Amino acid sequence: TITVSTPIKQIFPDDAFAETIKANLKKKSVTDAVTQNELNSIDQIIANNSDIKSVQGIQYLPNVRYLALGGNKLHDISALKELTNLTYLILTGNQLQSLPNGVFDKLTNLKELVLVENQLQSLPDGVFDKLTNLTYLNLAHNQLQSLPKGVFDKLTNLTELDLSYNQLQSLPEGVFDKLTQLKDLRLYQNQLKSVPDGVFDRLTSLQYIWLHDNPWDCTCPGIRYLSEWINKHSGVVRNSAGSVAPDSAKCSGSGKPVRSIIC
Ligand SMILES: [Mg+2]
Image (cartoon, rainbow, N blue to C red):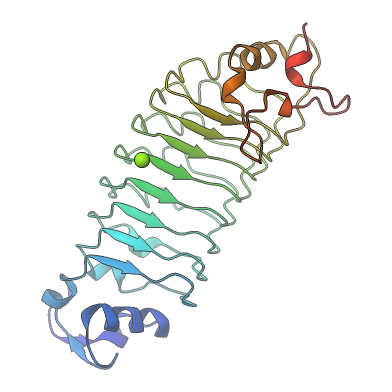
């Protein structure tokens, strides 16, 4: 906490973010000195496309519930770790290359986490484990080559998961086993050659899946599970136009539909 009144711009050294705070507080200048009681009044921050390089100071905003920081130049989110009241965190289009272990462990009220269009290469084991109220996780347009074993296991409330436009080489065995509420799963535009046997079997609520634009390896017998699953659930598979398209999972090399192959 801030113990003595202090200029907005000292607490929030990034010029653009200090201006966000000033406007939210209805203060007249970023040189105005502010109190912790004033900072306690902030219930959300909506600062998309604002050239923000740093959110240093945000740690003094304990009551922030909705945080939208899309389209800035953020490379560190250390300062968010204490924002225990956060329910929506939108970090689209920043320059995060990693998530330090633990960064989200106190964010237990989070319902939606949007990490689209960052440069995340990998995730630490258990990074999402405390996000037990999470319903929407969006990791699309990152650089992920793998997922940790068990990374979604604690996210039993998850209803949408978007992994599209990464470079996933494989999925861990069992990775979706706890996701019994998941309705919408996007895996399109990755580098998947295969999925684990049974990988969709616990997805009792699944209504929509995207599998297109992966270089599926249709060699037998490896492809049997996927081919069988698509045929059994053909109405669930969608293309990029959003239409029902079970043939949109294609064999790399032959180009024919995965679901046409009988081992
Ligand atoms: Mg929802």
